[PDB]
Every structure is written in C-alpha cells, then in structure tokens.
Amino acid sequence: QTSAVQQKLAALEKSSGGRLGVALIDTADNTQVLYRGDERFPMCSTSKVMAAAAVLKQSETQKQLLNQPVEIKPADLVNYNPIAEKHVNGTMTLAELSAAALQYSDNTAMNKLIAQLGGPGGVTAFARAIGDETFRLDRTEPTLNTAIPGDPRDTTTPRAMAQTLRQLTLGHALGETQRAQLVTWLKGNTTGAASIRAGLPTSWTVGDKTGSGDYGTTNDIAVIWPQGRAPLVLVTYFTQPQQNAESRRDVLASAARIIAEGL
Ligand SMILES: *[B]([O])([O])[C][N]C(=O)/C(=N\OC([C])([C])C([O])=O)C1=[C]SC([N])=N1
Image (tube, rainbow, N blue to C red; front, top):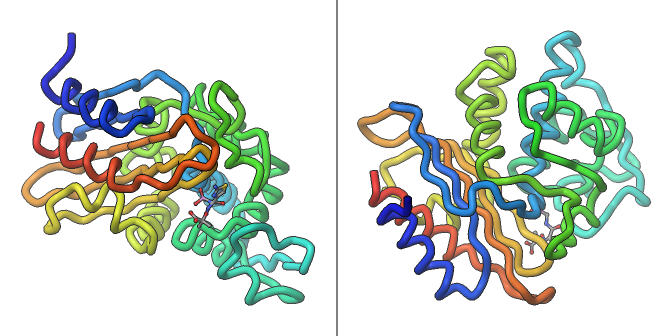
C-alpha cells in the first residue's frame, strides 16, 4: 500500500536529509493522499490559523469583537513583530491582530489572539470543539517554535491539520461570513510564494499559512483552487535533525509538485 506518489515523496525526503509529512484532501471526491500522515510535527506559525479561527468563532456571538482594541506594550514584543511594533503604546483591533498574525506571521499578534482565548489551552479547546482531537497548543510565542524532536508540545499531524483546514475554510466549522474572512486572510498571505505555491501551476489560486522554527522546521498549510476542478487542501510539514538547520521551503514546493503531478 505504497503509491507512486508516496514513493516519490519518500525519495524527496531521503535526499532532503529531514522528515517530511504530507496530507492532501481532494474535495472533488474526498480522497486523500498521505505521507507520514499520522506522525506528529511541530506546527510553528501554522498554528496561527487555529487561533484566528477560534477568535472568529467567538465573533459569531459578538458582532463588535473584531473591532475591539487590544493594548500593545513594549514588553509585549517578542522575536518577530513587524506589525505590532508600529502600535507599541497604542492598540490593535482583534481583526488587525488576526490579519497581522496570518498575513505577516507577527508573533506578538499571535500572543494577543492566544490571550483572547484564555491561553494556549483555549486554542486547543477550539480545535476539539470542531472535531480535531490531535492538535495541541501548549505555549505562547516564541517558545512554541522550539520544534524539538520527540517533543509533543505544539504539534499536530498532517492528517488532522488537513481535515481541520478543510472544515474551517470550505466546510461549516465557522459561520459563512467568518469562513469568508478566514479565506480572504489566507489568500492575502505575504509569506507563501516559495512554499506550496511554488510547486503548483501558477494559474491556481492559493490561500496559505507558512511556519518556521528551530530544527530548520519549514511548514505550509494551504487551501487551493485549481483551474478546472474542485478545491484541494494540502499540508506540508518538514523538520530536520540539527537545531540550527536552515529553512527548506524548496522541499515543500517539491512535495506540492509531486502531489500535483499525481492528480
Ligand atoms: B512562524 O513559524 O512563522 C514564527 N516564526 C518564528 O518565530 C521564527 N522565524 O521567523 C522568521 C524570523 C520570520 C523567519 O526567519 O522565518 C523562528 C522561531 S525559532 C526559529 N529558528 N525561527
């Protein structure tokens, strides 16, 4: 039970020196393609989709929540804050925080989403509420990116994340307006052109959230609207043996290319 596609992904992984995890859902026929689909990987910033979605869910019963100001203080800045540092000693709304977290991967923005949900466990609780029994968020930014091999903290599986991303962006885990907002945010991501998108035909529309961390952890989760067919959901996770390993977005592109060529 090893397909040509899975054999190619194994070949790619071997040449990469690291560990690769892939999960595809083709929503035309609901079929799946997985590679290490039930192994755990550090999420790094791909976890920001779950936090933003959790806040969107809260906004379904609070029409003004996304307009609520949140104070940003100097002490709130962490390792990567390109948007929040512009608002120090001021405020950002929860919408602005969601956009910054998703489209620029601002880590201070993520921490405010996590706080709005009552801590990392509030993010996990939302995951469980929408059927994901695998996701776990245990820490805030920036320590949730330590990505230590064998550490279960702040991990999920490719299979679980693909399923959840489908429910969030194409399914009914969120209200219609909230689903549309999440899709809009993902489609406007600034960080993804070298990752999954780089492996797919350019005519296709992609909405994604990247992740980066220690152990050269390089991730991307995407919803894809190909030319001429139903949407796809694709998760590509990659992590390496050495703590100081360099980013390998090319490996994610290569995985996406193999998946696309298998359609
Ligand atoms: B998320 O995974 O996109 C947040 N990423 C990080 O905090 C890390 N790097 O982010 C920048 C600075 C944008 C990058 O160079 O990829 C990070 C945390 S630990 C590590 N080695 N890099």
